[PDB]
Image (cartoon, rainbow, N blue to C red):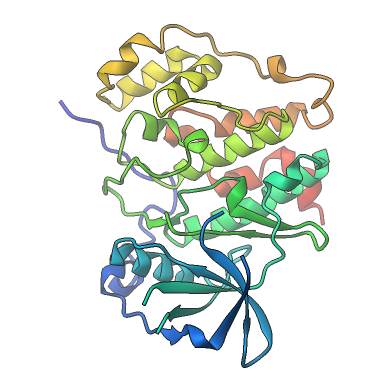
Length: 322
């Protein structure tokens, strides 16, 4: 009879109460500079280190690929709307070749969370997770879902304990009732709502992704849900979260499940986190880390922690004391 509708547990109407201009990005007017203000220095897609040949300033220039003209306006609008926010990357300028569009960013000391968390201490993890949550709670509070949260999109300046949530090209504004594309995040980070094609999702989407990072980080298991396609991904999840909850979730929202799944999910218990623990990763695992982790990875998007809630978990007790 059709999927049950859903609302965001928080920041539900922040967009409704704002000026049309804020979220109506199709009508945004972009004004371009000439790239002849920048020289390309060095060069995993089309992005470069560059300088401003008028202020000798180091920048990063990201030449966009041919993509629907609205999606550019969207990314630009979202970047402007979030400029100045905690741990959000900073758009410096927008230029064309004198004619492909490029975004110019403040220079960050690049080290994606991947090439780093393979060496982090229990404390660092907590610390940077709190930094990501600062950035997630901000944009969520600002009516925005980053929809591609993953290590490759978190730049860390480990020397200066600095962090930036980057790459807002999949980001969208949250509007209660709207049905979004389920074809968004990276495979290993897609939330269940995406795998079962439930389009009325929200900011919660991001907390699943966060959950997937926290998991791979503490259990030292890169690709914690290592699916081989968008169907086997839900199977790898089921083998951990069990199928009973999965199915209650389907029922709760009256979700039509793809004919395919009928023959692969099967039956599965909800494994205990302890079964992922061992001598290599035990120093990162803790009763709180696991309590916290468990509250992120829920089939039901409504029952996941909000970013603000997460920041108030005992897992961060030590960090927030600063």
